[PDB]
Image (cartoon, rainbow over all chains, first blue to last red; front, side, top):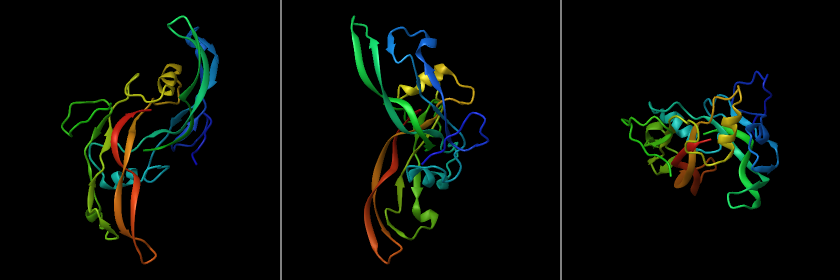
Length: 108
Length: 108
């Protein structure tokens, strides 16, 4: 169970923030739908033991290698979105596209 | 397909480095076997488009939110190891433990 934060949050630890990706703003007319979607992002500190899915992470923290800046804050749960778009073969394609939305953030 | 680096590598981009976790050095006598194992770690920069498993990552990079320090370098492939250990119920347990070894590093 991860943390969710608004932009004004005082939370420094690894957290999921809201963010809309706007294909229309990008100028991507090859995408028919959706024109924009809630993608979110991860940001925040990953101190000892915090929000770690894998047992690996804390073992490496204790082994304490010199060349490591420690774990960092990335997505731990992802979800797809459905898209309708033009391809480069003169067709309109419908697809469920995996790995488009961040649902949770954690440290590894 | 990720990058593998030795400690003296001049590679600045997200890369997997070798690292041994030594349970004996930790003093963890509750672990019978293995006494140590090759765990590895990830470290390196995650610039635009580099080593990204999910389409999400580059879309957020282009959306360019202020509160984001961009994607970072974490494990993208993990593997288990088998362990024999004492529990806290006066038993010796054998188990295949997931998420113990980093096999590949990437940016998200």
